[PDB]
Amino acid sequence: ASQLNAVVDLQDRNTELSYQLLLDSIGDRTRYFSMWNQAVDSYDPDVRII
Amino acid sequence: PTHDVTTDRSQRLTLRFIPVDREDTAYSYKARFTLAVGDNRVLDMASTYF
Image (cartoon, rainbow over all chains, first blue to last red; front, side, top):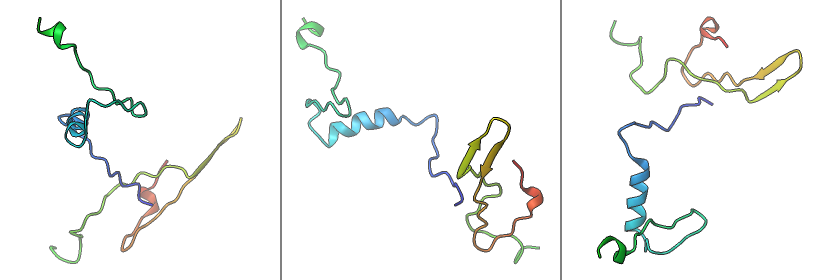
């Protein structure tokens, strides 16, 4: 009707990091969900720290 | 004048209208809009343009 845009997006917002930290809080982040390609970046602890 | 001239509610000056239906003929181009004038508003069509 008006095409009043409900999305006011700012450059100093970080939507991606706000969603990576969100899935940490509301779920077991170690689990793999192929539909959202939800597979967290994880190093090997014997490779980082010898 | 301070009263009964300009509103104090939420209302845009310029609205953007995207075509509901369009057609790209080989010699013409049709664009059909919804020119929705909201409640308690007036639109002089001289301010309207494509």
